[PDB]
Amino acid sequence: IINGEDCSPHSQPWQAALVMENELFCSGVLVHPQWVLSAAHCFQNSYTIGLGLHSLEADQEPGSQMVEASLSVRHPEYNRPLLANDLMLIKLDESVSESDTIRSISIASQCPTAGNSCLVSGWGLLANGRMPTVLQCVNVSVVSEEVCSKLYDPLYHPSMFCAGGGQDQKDSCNGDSGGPLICNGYLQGLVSFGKAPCGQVGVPGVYTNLCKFTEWIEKTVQA
Image 1: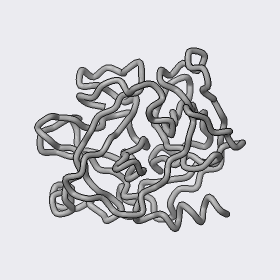
Image 2: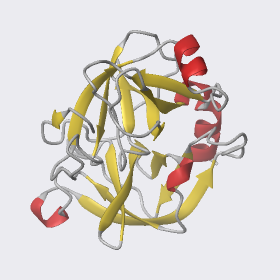
Image 3: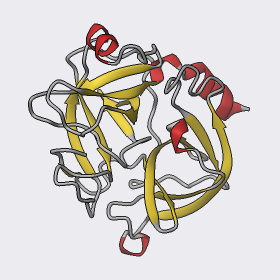
Image 4: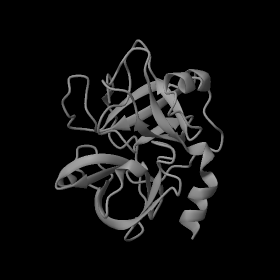
């Protein structure tokens, strides 16, 4: 997260950490007591998932859980075309009992509105290139489809939308992939990709356009 701040602890109780070999490589979002939504490009054969975290040390985060998962359902058109449809569902090995620090979030049914202020959170790199010790939060504004489509031509696909890109250089960065973009209290997007370097004036980041996928998400969790 570029030019954000520490989240208030446990203010984003849907945030999931995806870790392997004791290192975070992606986030995800709890969307059901037994299901984490993440970017398909974060796919692994299995996952160690940290829920209820703030720092990444579960022993220092009372109420947190480290759980295992191995069933992934990538979207059936993930990466067709290149970078599109960047979402997958991870089935936890057991349901979590939700709490004030581990809680699912509802997915937006309405598509994003240009100009609206949203929140993105994650443990990815800071403006100084270092990794934060605790979950970071920053506000970014949704950008219009015409701006997104021209800036990311020819890879722009309706499975994508853009947010950020302001002179304030508030943006997502490496390591934030798969984490949430919250708009009006609903899960609107997942961090997907952006042009390098992070935090460029005039370059928004690309987010998975979850309003397009509610049927596939619901059918997958229900099946």
